[PDB]
Image: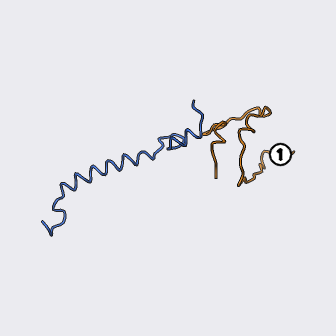
Amino acid sequence: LSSTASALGKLQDVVNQNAQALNTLVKQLSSNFGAISSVLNDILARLDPP
Amino acid sequence: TRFASVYAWNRKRISNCVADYSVLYNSASFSTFKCYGVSPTKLNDLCFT
């Protein structure tokens, strides 16, 4: 157990999957989905309410 | 006093200015002031490199 690499591969897989999903979720926050900009503060400072 | 022709449209770089957009925009002489991606009243609350 000490020497072999990836002996705990299953727990590592669980953690990696969860962290990867979160990383994707935060990354998607950067995409603008076609809007003018991906920052709400930018849109609100730039554009009128309507 | 004299703008360039349409085909040969001149350009000028503006830098280090303080832009009093609100006092310009509210003037009555402009027949149209359409803006895109930005709103005219907000323009003072902004700053463009």
User: What's the chain of the residue with tag 1?
Assistant: B
Query: A27 left or right of B48?
Result: left
Q: How is the image coloured?
A: by chain
Query: A14 left or right of A34?
Result: left
The image quadrant that residue A44 belongs to is top right
Residue at 45% x, 47% y: name it.
A30
Return the residue at label 1. B3
Which residue extends farthest left? A1
The colour assigned to chain A within the rendered structure:
blue
Residue at 72% x, 52% y: name it.
B14
Residue at 19% x, 62% y: name it.
A6
Residue at 68% x, 35% y: name it.
B34
Q: Quadrant of the N terminus of chain B?
A: top right
Please, what is the three-letter code of the amino acid marked with disc 1?
A: Phe
The colour assigned to chain B within the rendered structure:
orange
Which residue is nearer to you in this view: B33 or B41? B41
Which residue is nearer to you in this view: B8 or B15? B15
Q: Position of residue B8 (x, y in %)?
A: 78, 50
